[PDB]
Length: 27
Length: 27
Image (cartoon, rainbow over all chains, first blue to last red; front, side, top):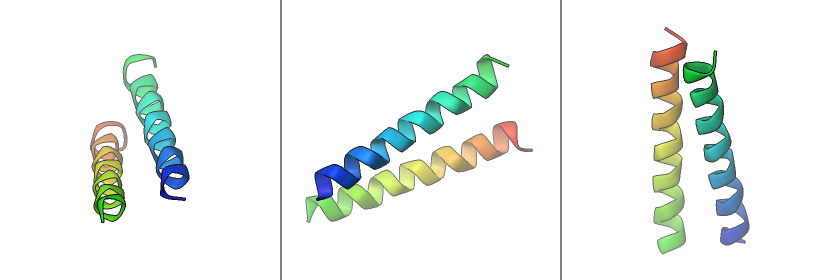
């Protein structure tokens, strides 16, 4: 189960990085 | 034990990303 939860958390960190890069250099 | 320490380090990186995004686009 650690691979599933860790893939979910890495997806969340990737989404937060994309949103922060969006609010920084896309708005 | 690698899953435990790696989940802790990913949580720390997520918290640092949240704090840096806070100081950038929330202050």
